[PDB]
Image (cartoon, rainbow, N blue to C red; front, side, top):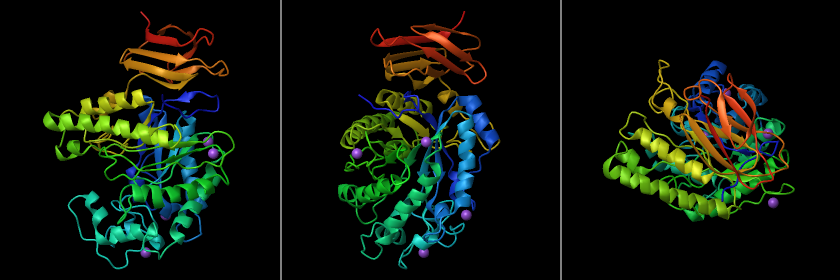
Length: 449
Ligand code: NA
Ligand code: NA
Ligand code: NA
Ligand code: NA
């Protein structure tokens, strides 16, 4: 059965939010094009309680050994917006195709970029190997200069043992700033690791795991309590193949706080431009295969919690809502958190460029338990109902906290199996208390007559 991240009250967290935001990748100041008013809109429309907040190595460490505390001030400012609205934050050290420094035309400055993004220019060593224009961005991964930049980072070439050490110490700098931040729950060490010339389990169990171990150790010099979240290699594994990632040791006193944060991008959904016919058949197989592989690696890592850190699609495609609902149902059964890709404007996201909602908003805006006083064994919801079964824990005194959308709960609530402590119609938060002396408790929440 699944394991959960916990809040300071000991409640088990069911995490629902977005990646915010891809616009940070190219921004000179490292910040997403996302305001406090945008967060208020998100919360009002969907009741989210989590964010995978994109940060970047190029912003943390713009020159070797010279950390930018002003950038960290900016991150802290945004984290405060989230804190004020009761969100938990996972910071993602984000890259795609290594760096903006992989081409001159795509480099928005010092490794920032709209396509390639992440590492600072000083950490990018392509050794003069070419990077030719490609018709979709993912193809840059296999261009010679990008492959070489990764091979140098992982020190496959033997020429750059320092780069992983810089990466680990950049994470330590972030962790030193955020250790005492009560809204931060997780550090996602690297978006979509790619091995370059080294592929599969030899990469994952070799230099990838070694970087995760070094970085975990560095973070634990300054932060004992934040969950350290590790990803498999993305290529193949995103598409349903197994990971060879191996266990990371957590030097913290007591129980380990490592979590697993894989992504889900079925190939048939992409190539088929939607979720109908044989593409749907094969995407459903992918989801199920992915679930089994994800559960396996989460066991290997020490029976750890899971966060689906990224998944998404163009919501206008045939079958999109069915796909989204399938993924969220799977995450629910797995006890997984979810950060959807992404909050950015356009048909993948919740809002179009003019601020109009896509179908994503209504799809995501469902009741869910946010923080449960005990282990949630099973739950379900529809627009106007939620049911939740809880394995009791008498040590927890904080109430179970549940989001109820206005759409289905226009007035008061009726709760079977628990006492209502609070029903805040402004914040949309229901708080309930359940007995801890009668075994597993089932709570059913419906609109008042
Ligand atoms: Na900058
Ligand atoms: Na460079
Ligand atoms: Na924290
Ligand atoms: Na340990």
